[PDB]
Image 1 (spheres, protein in one colour):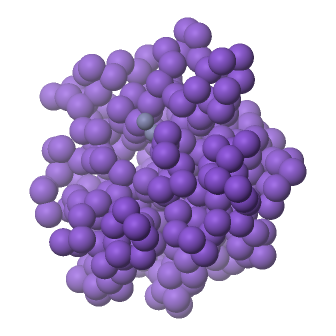
Image 2 (cartoon, helix red, strand yellow):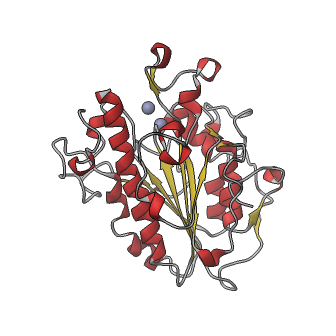
Length: 312
Ligand SMILES: [Zn+2]
Ligand SMILES: [Zn+2]
């Protein structure tokens, strides 16, 4: 219904330059201040720390404090100041734009769903990875809960099916959603014990996300010969863990504590892509996601031209 980027155009197409392949990990309930890179006293991201090419952003603010509110905003043209959750799904979003310009879009979801973001695109481009019908990694724990790494299975098939095209893959993580954080990770990540126990479980869940992001990057690396590959991670909101008597998330922005809106963001790219990240301490928000995705595929749109991205 409401358009934002009818003028959008891709400056270069994949027939005259290397095609581009991006994984966008849409994170869940992760707090910036529980990231080792941001000064946390526990090493919650030990695998990512060993990977060259990873930029950590230390000053990122979410649009809101819930999945329902934040996720459509992350893909919106409006920005946090203008965003309206009720009317979001009736507006053209950045995936609509990229799809129209020929970028192959895939959304795998181990969270809930895309909160309206994928609704205008063909049903076949969204896939529910919360069920063992699609996810091959579900029986590794007492709860039979499907794991985020299951979303990486068979992604080569998608690349093959779309070979030579630009591709953007969204992987919507279960991540750190609670309150039962101890359910969110398999036993091999139960590092911080006992499961304060609530904090420990929270940090163990971050370890499993560290693992998932690291494996996402490794998967991308295997395609770097044929594709310009990059990985963007941003959490949809943080989490209160008892500060001032506040717990969980979803607090209205007017009263939301810092903990619920201070989120981690990472960017990784292969050396050959020529993509340059912004400074780690750039003042950033969820508003930066749409311009970042457009830039990664060499797309310009009038509405977002003044906007700061995660990359130059
Ligand atoms: Zn939630
Ligand atoms: Zn969420």
